[PDB]
Image (cartoon, rainbow, N blue to C red):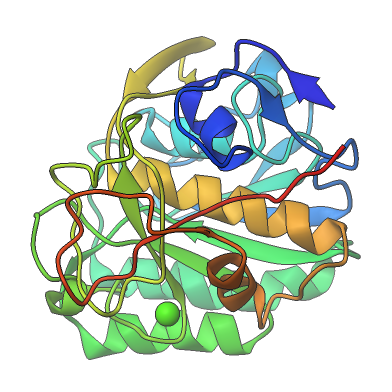
Length: 279
Ligand SMILES: [Ca+2]
């Protein structure tokens, strides 16, 4: 399948060179996989989700995304026009309030909730969790991400936006999950992206068009935007049978475009997520 005039990040993950505008992908498109987006919520009624999104848990007064961030991330995972895995099932867990903030105890509870709730859902091709959030180092937050990964869920987390070593941030610094940096459309490390030895992979993160609240769209930037490209790619590859939740991050690194990014500090991987599609 081919989507013409796609957002640049979708084109980039299906190409070995920058500057293309078509997203090439297998028609299975993540069908039969499930992705939990742990964030400010998801506007499930947005037409771009086609009925495939549902809120399953909130830690605040409403399950509504009053911010937009969670709806943007979910759109990069799985919306029709803006998504990597266009037929996956999206589940929203609201651990962040409508200003985008949340306490660590609530974020940990939301991770432990997903590890249990996936056992009540029909996800025959596997389960992914996308965490476009973080803050300063906390061994407890890291331990919650490690538990979620151990339970059989592919965990992708944002590296953070401080132009610093991600070892000082959580859950970015948990080694067992998949920590995602950001790149721009000229194959530079995004100027805000964290870096360091804990990073596993880069994905597109600057000027990313996706869904927004009020049935709208908008373009924003962050490692929060790179993480759902990798979470969606994992769901897509699991549905194709190429990998499992336990080994998807390593499979994505092994099959990445290698050495194409500029402005990568020595000691950080130079790997850009790539779907290896061949018509
Ligand atoms: Ca890792």
